[PDB]
Amino acid sequence: IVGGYTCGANTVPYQVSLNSGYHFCGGSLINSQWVVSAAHCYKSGIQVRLGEDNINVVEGNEQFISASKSIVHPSYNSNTLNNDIMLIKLKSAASLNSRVASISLPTSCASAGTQCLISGWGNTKSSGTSYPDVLKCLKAPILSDSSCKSAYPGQITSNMFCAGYLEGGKDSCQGDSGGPVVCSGKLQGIVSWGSGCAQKNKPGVYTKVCNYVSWIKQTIASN
Ligand SMILES: [Ca+2]
């Protein structure tokens, strides 16, 4: 997250870190057994880390639970990043309390102008590299479909939306991928892609979670 703020420990209780020996992507806990992330974060051997603030220090609220199964969206296209969503099942159910909690799925799609909370452990610099150990946060609005398409000609599908600031300086970034965009207490986006980070006229692009609620529910119901 570039141009954000330190969230505070366990203030984003649905945020998870995907770990394969190291943090590599975010995700969102949607029930005791299941995490939403980006399909482009797929790999084998995932350990889901819940209750994290500093990802390099054991602070006392963590739950580390190996994944039993990953399910990339049936229509994920890694070239275009269309349908950049996956589900990860935990080998055992997480214990839920105020610091580790699921986030609700949307019942309707959010609108341009709505304020959301984007979070992650990704790079905090737009030029060069610095990775935080504690969770960063950014409040940002959803942008119009027209301004999103004008920013990224030929690239924005109906399964994507832009959020952030066209002036630059505030955005998600590498290492945030797969993490949440939460608006009015609902998971509306997944950190997906963008041109660089926090560049002028290059806002963040997010998977549009409301399009996937029926797939998510039916997949969980049978897996
Ligand atoms: Ca920790």
Image (cartoon, rainbow, N blue to C red):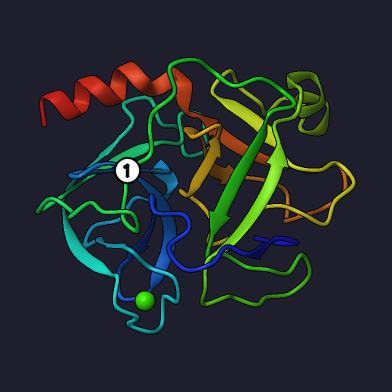
Q: Is mark 1 within 8 Å of ligand 1?
A: no
Residue positioned most to the bottom: 57
| Residue 77, image x, y percentages | 45, 32
Using the image as rendered, state which of residue 125 and residue 184 is in the foreground: 184
Position of the N terminus by quadrant: bottom right
For numbered disc 1, what is the local secondary structure?
A: loop
Picture coordinates of residue 214, whole percent (x, y) = 31, 16
Left or right, 161 with respect to 189, comes to right
On-image quarter of the C terminus: top left
Q: Position of residue 154 (x, y in %)?
A: 72, 25
Is residue 221 left or right of 28 when viewed as pictured? Answer: left
Q: Quadrant of ligand 1?
A: bottom left
Most foreground residue, 60 or 141: 60
Give me the residue at 14% from left, 24% from top.
221
Residue at 29%, 26% (x, y): give it. Answer: 216
Which residue was labeled with disc 1?
102
At x 76%, y 65%, the residue is 126
Q: Going by the picture, which residue comes out furthest to the front?
A: 98
Instruction: Give left or right: position of 1 versus 135.
Output: right
Number of numbered discs visible in the structure rendering: 1
Left or right, 100 with reference to 70: right
Q: Is residue 96 above or below residue 113?
A: below
Amino acid type of the residue tagged 1 in the rendering: Ser
State the residue at coordinates (73%, 48%). 195
Mark 1 residue crowding within 10 angstroms, few (<14) / some (14–19) / many (20+)? many
Estimate the x, y position of residue 70 in percent, counting from the top left. 22, 44
Q: From what the image shows, is residue 66 above or below residue 209?
A: below
Which of the 4 quarters of the picture holds residue 94?
bottom left
